[PDB]
Image (cartoon, rainbow over all chains, first blue to last red; front, side, top):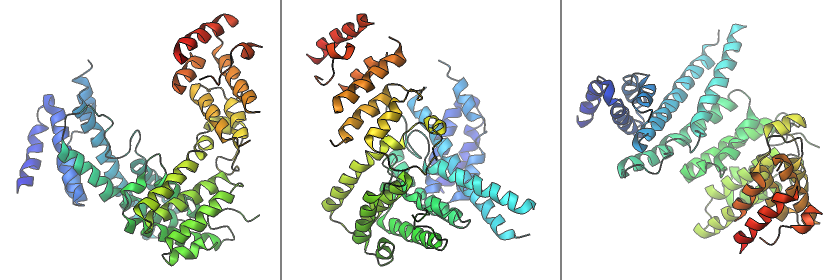
Length: 225
Length: 184
C-alpha cells in the first residue's frame, strides 16, 4: 500500500533525465526493502525500470561527484551483481536437470559463469557488497541499517549456493577453500554469519572432505606423501 | 585426523583444536596451511567459546594470518616467472620471501614490496642487519637516485644505517639530513 505508491512513482522519476540520480537513489531504496524480505522478483521488476544507461547519464551531469550519488551508483551495481548471481543460478540449475556433445559444453559454461557471479557478490571490489566506499555522505541511519542487514540476509545464502555449485560438479577442493574465503580477515565475511550458518557451512564442507578421501586424497584434496 | 569427526559430533572447540594444530605442522603446501587455519578459525567462531576466550583465540590467529599474508601477497607475475604452482608451493620462511620480494626479477617492485620484506625481519626468529641493508640498498637501485623516501615516511628509527650503508652519495646525505630533522 505505502510501497506500491513509491514503485508506481519510479516511472515518473525515470521520465526526466535531469533527475536521474534521484531515480537511482529511490530505486535503490525500494529494492533494499524488497531484498530485505527475500522478494527477488519484486525487486527485479523495479530494476528493469532503471534505463540501463542511467549511470553514464549521471556521470555526464557532472564532469566537474556527490557522496550520496557515488553511493547510489555503487549500491545500484551491488544490487545488480546480486540479481545476476541468482538468475544465473536458476539458469544453471535448470540445465543441471534437463539431461538431453554440445550439452556438457554448455554446462561447464554455466557452472563457470555462476561461480563468477557468486564470487562477484561475495568479494565485491573495494569494500564488499552493500558497503559504502564514501564516508563523507550525509547521515542516513535507515539506509545504513538496511545495508548491514542485507549482508546478513543475502551473503550467507550465496555462500551455500556456491558450495552446492562446486560440490554438485566435483570441485571439492575449492569447496574447502570457502573456509579461506569466509574467515579471511580481508573481508570478514565470517562476521555476517550466524553461528547456525557457520555450523551449516562446516557440515557441508565435511561432506566435501568425505568425497575427497573417497578419491585417495587428503581431506583438503592434497596428495599423501 | 580427528577434526573430521569432532565436527560431525558438534565438538567444535575440539575440531578447532586439532585443526589449529595440523595448521601449524603444515609446511608442504601453503594453500593447505591457509585452508586448515581458515577452517580452524571457523570452528572457533562457530563454537561455544567464552566471549573473551573466543576473542582471545581469534586474537592469536589474526597473528598467524598476519604472517601468511606476506606469501599470500606475492605478485602473480613474480610467481608466473619463477614458474611456481599458483597454489601448490610450500609454506616458505621469512628468509625465502625476502629473497623474492627483493629479487631483481621482481620488476614492478615498489615501496610496498620492500616494506613487506622489512617487516619480514621480525619473523626471522634467530645476521638480521645485513639483510636490512641488502634489502635497503636494492630499493635505491630501482629508483636510480621517490621510494627509499616513501619507505621511511611509512615507518614513521636508529635501526637504519648511514655512513656504513655507503661503505651517488650526494642525495644519500641529503636524505640522511632530512632524516635528522625527522627522527629528532
